[PDB]
Image (tube, grey):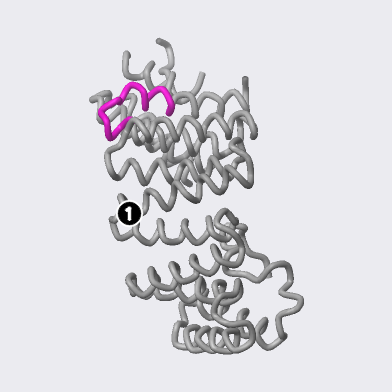
């Protein structure tokens, strides 16, 4: 019944209140079968809604673009990449024509082309599409909106795949700046963006800068519960009488990361500490 704002370009404005009930049902079935990956049913029904809609309002209409966008994504999941790119451009052309060059639906379609090219390793081609979507999101939502930040994270990983590390660090820091000011410092996106930037640092050999971000994430996590963390204990075990001295999903990964890093550093007692603490945090 409900759908993410990220897939809004696959749905009719508001209800679709004035869309004939037949075309509304036909749309819901296309969506339903495509979810189950049952493309035998999904495609004809889509081709039919497309045919039915072209008769009613012509090819250059927002609803044609909607059914094209749905179909284009079915073709992409079928690994029919060239066909998918064609429909999305056709859908882009219509949306530019009927809704404006800087409409949210346009940004959505560009983010679909960029994803398609990127997942096919055509990062250079994807990059401007992603940047146009970002210039649209800025215009519409404002330069400090969390959705503008979400977009920066996608652009930064697109640039990372091209080794453009100076642009990457900038985008990740701009996105972290937004998620820290516009959202809480204990918002999950803050830790997510930090791990992403830490990954970039790792590529570059900046192990110490990544170690810092892992520690920062693990500190605000502990300080939320009881304002020493697992890593201070790890560093204590690394350095080292009647009885012995016996002893969030975005955090469990950070523990796997810092454990991996300590191991990379050859700090094995500190590594085992976090590696064991990660296995515990998973279960």
Q: Quadrant of the N terminus?
A: bottom right
- Report x, y in % for residue 61: 59, 75
Magenta residues, as a range? 201-214
Q: Which residue is mark 1?
A: 125
Residue at (75%, 78%) from the top-left corner?
Answer: 18
Relative to 126, residue 36 above or below: below
Q: At numbered mark 1, what does the secondary structure look like: helix, strand or loop?
A: helix
Residue at (60%, 84%) from the top-left corner?
Answer: 53
Q: Nearer the viewer, residue 210 or 144?
A: 144
Relative to 98, residue 231 above or below: above
Is residue 212 one of those drawn in magenta? yes
- Report x, y in % for residue 283: 48, 47
Residue at (51%, 18%) from the top-left corner?
Answer: 228
Can you tell which quarter of the image residue 6 is in? bottom right
| Pointer 1 local density, CA inside 10 Å: few below 14, some 14–19, many at least 20 | few
Q: Nearer the viewer, residue 123 or 262?
A: 123
- Report x, y in % for residue 197: 40, 33
Relative to 6, residue 143 above or below: above
- Report x, y in % for residue 167: 37, 34
Q: Nearer the viewer, residue 14 or 40?
A: 14
Magenta span: predominant SS is helix
Is residue 249 one of those drawn in magenta? no
């Amino acid at each position: 019944h409900h759908h993410s704002s990220g897939r809004e370009n696959l749905y009719f404005q508001g209800g679709g209140y004035e869309i004939p009930a037949r075309l509304r049902t036909l749309h819901n079935l296309v969506i339903q079968y495509a979810s189950q990956g049952r493309y035998e049913v999904a495609v004809p029904l889509c081709k039919q809604a497309l045919e039915d809609l072209e008769k009613t309002s012509g090819h250059d209409h927002p609803d044609v673009a909607t059914m094209l966008n749905i179909l284009a994504l079915v073709y992409r999941d079928q690994n029919k990449y060239k066909d998918a790119a064609n429909l999305l451009n056709d859908a882009l052309a219509i949306r530019e024509k009927t809704l404006g060059k800087d409409h949210p639906a346009v940004a959505a379609t560009l983010n679909n082309l960029a994803v398609l090219y990127g997942k096919r390793g055509k990062y250079k081609e994807a990059e401007p599409l992603c940047k146009r979507a970002l210039e649209i999101r800025e215009k519409v939502l404002g330069k400090d909106h969390p959705d503008v930040a979400k977009q920066l994270n996608n652009l930064a990983l697109l640039c990372q795949n091209q080794g453009k590390y100076e642009e990457v660090e900038y985008y990740y820091q701009r996105a972290l700046e937004i998620y820290q000011t516009k959202l809480g410092p204990d918002d999950p996106n803050v830790a997510k963006t930090k791990n992403n930037l830490a990954s970039c640092y790792l590529k570059q050999g900046k192990f110490k800068q990544a170690e810092t971000l892992y520690k920062e994430i693990l500190t605000r996590a502990h300080e939320r519960e009881f304002g020493k963390p697992i890593w201070m204990h790890a560093e204590e075990r690394e350095e080292c009488t009647s009885f012995g001295e016996y002893g969030s999903p975005t955090v469990t990964t950070t523990l796997k990361n810092l454990g991996a890093l300590y191991r990379r550093q050859g700090k094995f007692e500190a590594a085992e500490t976090l590696e064991e603490a990660a296995m515990r945090s998973r279960k």
